[PDB]
Image: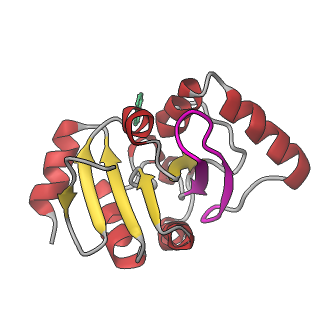
Amino acid sequence: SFSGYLKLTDNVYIKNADIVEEAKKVKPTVVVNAANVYLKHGGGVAGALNKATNNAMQVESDDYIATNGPLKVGGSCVLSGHNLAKHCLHVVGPNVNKGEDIQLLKSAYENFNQHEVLLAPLLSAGIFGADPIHSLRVCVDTVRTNVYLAVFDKNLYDKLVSSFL
Ligand SMILES: c1cnc2ncccc2c1
């Protein structure tokens, strides 16, 4: 199971780890992807998860978009987890760098409540442009299910833990 996670709250845990490597090791029921509305997994967590699936995640995502159209910012869809997890929950947090509404971050985290346990990144953090300290705060105040956060950056991980209220 999940190991080496620091407990933040009753249900939120955090570790300095590459979510791809965490996924290959744990093979959780659900890995969360930091998706965009088009499921175009180019960079950040999405690009890394997709590259780990040998592009099978992108092929599956393009078929999903061809059938269903784009997701909403704050929305999600459940697709295969391929070699990483049983399922991948593609969650669209607002991309501040693309001018999207930061108020949608709480709606994005509400998607996690449909799954008992998840391996996840901090939504809207990294190349999405939001303040990761704010994202962790919204996570612990929104998610009620068991969330194991993987923070790739060591220096950001230290900053998140040492500043956690
Ligand atoms: C490999 C490469 N880029 C990453 N970016 C964000 C999170 C995890 C990653 C792993």
Q: How does the figure colour the protein chain or chains? A: secondary structure
Of residues 71 and 112, the one drawn nearer to the viewer in this rendering: 112
At x 55%, y 31%, the residue is 47
Apparent side of residue 124 relative to residue 152 in the rendered image (left or right): right
Find residue 83 and report its horizontal and vertical position in percent.
57, 33
Q: Specify the quadrant of the image occupied by residue 76.
A: bottom right
Q: Does residue 75 show up magenta in the picture?
A: yes
Q: Where residue 10 appears, x then y in whole percent?
A: 25, 75
Judge left or right: residue 41 versus residue 24: right
Magenta-tinted stretch:
73-92
Q: To which quarter of the image does residue 138 belong?
A: bottom left
Residue 153 in percent (x, y) is at 26, 37
Does residue 1 sit above or below 146 in this rendering? above
Q: Nearer the viewer, residue 82 or 14?
A: 82
Name of the residue lying farthest toward the right: 67
Residue at image coords 49%, 54%: 96
Up/down of 99 relative to 38, above or below: below
Q: Which of 152/89 is in front?
A: 89
Q: In the rendered image of this protein, does residue 155 appear above or below residue 163? A: above
In the image, residue 56 lies at what x, y percent?
A: 69, 29
Q: Is residue 89 above or below residue 108?
A: above
Residue 131 in magenta?
Answer: no
Please tell me in which quarter of the rendered image ligand 1 is found. top left
- Quadrant holding the C terminus: bottom left
Res 131 seen here: no
Residue reaching furthest to the left: 162
Foreground pick, 158 / 57: 57
* Most distant residue in the top direction: 54
**Can residue 67 be seen here?**
yes
What residue is shown at x 34% (from left), y 53% (from top)?
149
